Each structure stands twice: as C-alpha cells, then as structure tokens.
Amino acid sequence: QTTTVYSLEDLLPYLKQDNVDVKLAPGTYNVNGFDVGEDRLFSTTPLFLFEGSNSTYDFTDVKLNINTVVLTKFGNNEVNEIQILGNNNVLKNLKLEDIGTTAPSNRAQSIVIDGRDNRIEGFHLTIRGSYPYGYGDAFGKGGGSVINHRKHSGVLIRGLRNHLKDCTIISRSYGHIVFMQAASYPTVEGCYIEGEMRSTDDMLAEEGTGSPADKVDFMTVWGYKLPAGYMMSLQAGGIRAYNAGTTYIDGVEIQRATDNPTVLNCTIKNARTGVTLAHANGTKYVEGCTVLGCENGYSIGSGTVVNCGADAIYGPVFKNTYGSDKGYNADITILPPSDAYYNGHDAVAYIGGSNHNLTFRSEITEIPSNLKIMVSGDLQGLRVLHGSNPSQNNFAGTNIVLRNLTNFPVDLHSDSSNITVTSCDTDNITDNGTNNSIEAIDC
C-alpha cells in the first residue's frame, strides 16, 4: 500500500497523516533559500515535521541537499531540518547533506526525535554551518560564552524508546553529533559518527591575525589561556547524554533527564567524547563500540561498558566523571593508535569514585612515556586545569577492582584507597594510596 511521490511538495502533506506508507522516489532534491517563505515550499521550521504516527517513509537513493542559508531564513529562531513528533514511525535510508557552511541565525539541529517508538535507520547525514567553527568549546558552549556561538548539532534523541540505527553521521559543524535530552530508553545502534580535529597549537598560531580567539587573547571559558599541546575536536560530543531537556509525547511537554540509554556496536571518530552517558539516570549500557581519536573514550558514570575499544592518541580511553561515580563496570581494549599521538592529558585513564570493576586490555608494546592509568590525582585534562570544572578532577577512589592487562603504568594517588590491582607487570606501578593491593599476573 506504498504511495510514491516525486517531489518534496507532494511529500509534505503525508507528514501530517497517520498510518501512511510513503516513498520519495530515488533522485536528488535541493532545498535553497528561495524555497523558504509564505508562498514557498517551506513556510515554517522544522522543514520536515513528522506529526503522524504508525507511518513508514522510504528515502532509498534519495539525496536531499539543504543549503545552509536556510538556517538563516527563519529569523532568530532555532531551525530543525527534521523533527518527529508522532509515534511508531520508521524513516529509512535518506542521504542528507548540508550545502555550504553558513551558520544558523540562532542554532540548528539536523534531526530531532520526540514522540515514542520511532526509528531512523540507514541515514547518511553530513552536518555543516555553525559559529564559531574552529575552536571546539574553548570559547563557550552555553551562556556567558567568551565567543558567542550559533551551534548546529546532528541528531537530538528525545522522547521514549527512540532508536537511531545503522546511520552514518558526519559533522563539520560546531555542535554535538548525536546527543540525548529528556530521552527515556534511547538506543543508538550500529552507527558511524565522525568529526574532525584541530590542535590547540594551531589555534594559538592565530596570534596577531585578529581572529576571534586572538581578540580575546586566547582566554578560554575554563579561566586560563588556551594551553598548547592538546588535540581538540571541532565538534562536541560523539554520543552525549544530558541530565535535562524538553520532549513532547502525545501532546504532553516533559522536562526530565535522559534515562536508561543503550549504545551498541557504534564507531565514533574525532569527537570531543566517544560515549558520555554519566548525566543520564537509570541503566547505562554500552557494548561493542570503537572510539578512535576522540578527546575522551568512555564516561558513563555508572553501569556497563563491555567489549569496547578506544585508542589513546588524543585523550584517555576512560574517565570517571565525578567522585560520586559508583558502580562503573568496564572492559575496555586500548586500541592501536589510529594516527600519531597528540595526548596532552598525560593519561590513558582517570579513575575515581567507588565500587568500580575495571578491566583494561591492550597489545600495545610502544607506550608513550606520558601515558599512565591514574587512580585519583590531578589530571592534566584540557578542561580541568587550574581548578576548572573542579568536581571533574582531584577526587578520591575507593573500593575499586583494577585489572590492568596492559603494559601501561599505573599511578595510585594518595587519595586512593582499597584499590585491588592486578597487572601484567607491577614494577611500573606507583602506590601512594592507603590499603591498596598490587599483585602480578602472567601474560
């Protein structure tokens, strides 16, 4: 009972209907500035507002090119390209590309998933257009920013039991790539998520150019001049959950934290973090993932990370977020480097909180001398120097199992206690903590 349409104009009325089975015919469809206006294709934002329920939309072999100037055609208002408000919808196989790099007038998201039991599968999304682009979050990601931002993020998962499956999300925009706000039981599965990087040294080389960073003398939002020797993503989170947000289900506005997120078989490359779910409540579960060249690998706060890998070229593979982290169980492989090392954090892992069970595995034999597993201590992390983000650094670790099946050294700080360490080698383990146990393992 599939209805096939051959233009965006004939597609739009179906987005208001329940129980439809619609296919946009293979082809290339362009959305330009002249398509936005009262008498034009798109009079309102979101451009594609899926209000119906129990519908299926087939975008196989559809290329949708959206000119980034459309992000400025709705005044000082947020522009979403796609938003799902209905329930039990399936959208599949769309290839969506932002054309050009024009920044939104306010902010933008490519896709916002509200409602319940929706699935977006097989999408290929290229995100462009944001301001400032080139600094990551160094000069602001919220209010009071050093440089005023106009962010543009990829997929915002909200609602209930919403599902992003087998998608490719490429971001060249300052914003999250995939993030969750007020989402209950979201699932991200089989996705490839990719940003790009820039060194802080390259940013500092803007001295004397009159760039926005040069005009503030490179003073970051963290309270200090941008330090040399770090590799930053130009994006925010690869997959990042919020402890806040607004969603809509069945007409009901809901403000709540993300809860019960699941991330399965995802690859995240060159983002600010691979998988960060520490701010979500409920059960956090991450399995089968690969994090490459991110500033941080896995930070879920509490729950399970199993059969996951990350390299350590730009940041630690593992970070406890706060000293209140409790019950973080993790089995992480430190992968061979995906590119040259540029890790100014001087750690492959930062461990704290209590009652964790942590296994690290690696076949790396060539260990850079600045890389160690830290239990407590003063992490030289880009965003936590000099008292910045104080709850995220310099906290105690107690009652933690640490199985170090790697050649990386371990430093147990004086704030660590009751750490049960097993390790391939114990000669490179420094123990300044209280009542820690260190035992050797064979190979």
Image (cartoon, rainbow, N blue to C red):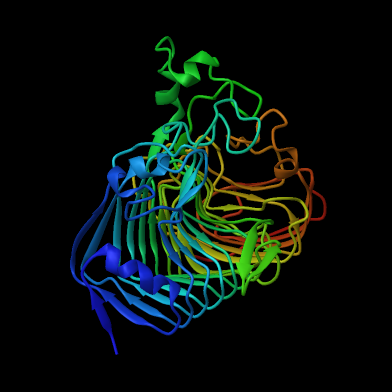
Residue visible at 31% across and 78% down in the picture: 22
Q: Give coordinates of residue 197: x percent, y percent.
A: 39, 39
Given residues 324 and 208, the one toward you in this image is 208
Q: Can residue 286 be seen here?
A: no
Q: Is residue 197 left or right of residue 181?
A: left
Rendered position, 381 above or below 226: below
Relative image position of residue 114 (x, y in whole percent) = 55, 67
- Outermost residue on the bottom side: it is 1
Please determine whether, in this image, residue 390 is positioned above or below residue 10. Answer: above
Q: Quadrant of residue 357?
A: bottom right
Q: Is residue 290 visible?
A: yes
Q: Quadrant of the N terminus?
A: bottom left
Which residue: 28% across, 44% down?
34
Q: Indicate the position of residue 12 as horizontal and vertical percent values.
A: 35, 67
Instruction: Choose between 137 and 99: the one closer to the eye.
Output: 99
Residue 116 is situated, as x and y percent measured from the top left of the image, at: 56, 75
Instruction: Tell me what residue is drawn at x 44 percent, y 53 percent.
Output: 44
What residue occupies the far top of the structure in this picture? 208
User: Is 40 in front, or is 184?
Assistant: 40
Quadrant of the rendered structure where residue 20 is? bottom left
In the image, taking residue 418 as reference, residue 255 lies left or right, namely: left
Task: Single out the residue that lies furthest toward the left.
Answer: 27
| Furthest residue in direction front, as rendered | 39
